Amino acid sequence: GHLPKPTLWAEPGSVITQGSPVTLRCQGGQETQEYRLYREKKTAPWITRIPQELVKKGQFPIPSITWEHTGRYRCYYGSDTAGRSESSDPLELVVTGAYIKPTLSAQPSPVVNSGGNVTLQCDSQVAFDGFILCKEQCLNSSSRAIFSVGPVSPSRRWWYRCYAYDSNSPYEWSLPSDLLELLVLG
């Protein structure tokens, strides 16, 4: 048989502010209907609540996301009996807004030359053991983290936001830092 691995994504995205809606989506074959979504390590009861009418379209909506929804998800279609596809690449569903927002700055500055590298610093008013830098994807880093980005170029937009988080609950992030725009001389 041949049941290609499905694509899994979230709308509007995988990083959602607490209380906002998000819909996880799975795309298998053109006629696929037997979609299955699941969370790694801990079962997600909210999935069992999804109407079959939506499941068949690969739609798994969360009207108002909460801390309980966060986690690593994967989807596949079919069954052991009828035959199933491999599981999709993982999607890390994260909720933001759990902590005060950090500040993001560029060193030496936000204005750099094409081809140059810049250091981005995420500073928090209090201690956190983890920081995230997302390009508006994201990457992981006692109240500040340093990230290196580049080579930068004028042909692309360089917008960033950073977050602070606690390693004991890695899928819940702080409020996002203000957006930082790098200006590339070019």
Image (spheres, helix red, strand yellow):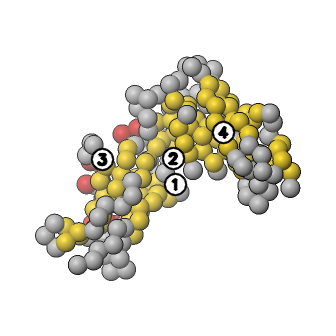
| Image depth: mark 4 or mark 1 in front | 4
Location of residue 90 in the rendering, given as x and y in whole percent from the top left corner: 39, 54
Residues tagged 4 and 3 counted as in contact (Cβ below 8 A): no
> Any mark on residue 40, and which?
3
- Disc 1: which residue: 13
Amino acid marked by disc 1 = Gly
Whichever of callouts 2 and 4 sits on the residue coming sooner in the sequence is 2
Count all numbered tags in the image, as a single digit.
4
> Any mark on residue 16, and which?
2
Q: Cα distance, mark 2 to mark 1? A: 7 Å
Amino acid marked by disc 3 = Glu
- Disc 4: which residue: 148
Q: Residue at x 53, y 38 (%)?
A: 140
* Quadrant containing the C terminus in the rendered view: bottom right
Whichever of callouts 4 and 3 sits on the residue coming sooner in the sequence is 3
Whichever of callouts 4 and 1 sits on the residue coming sooner in the sequence is 1
| Image depth: mark 2 or mark 4 in front | 4
The image quarter containing residue 6 is bottom left
Q: Is residue 63 above or below residue 83?
A: above
In the shown orientation, is residue 114 left or right of residue 52? right
Location of residue 157 in the rendering, given as x and y in whole percent from the top left corner: 73, 55
Q: Cα distance, mark 3 to mark 2? A: 19 Å
Q: Residue at x 46, y 43 (%)?
A: 94
Location of residue 18 in the rendering, given as x and y in whole percent from the top left corner: 49, 41
Amino acid marked by disc 2 = Ile
Q: Residues within 10 Å of mark 1 (few under 14, many from 20)?
A: few
- SS of the residue at dot 2? strand
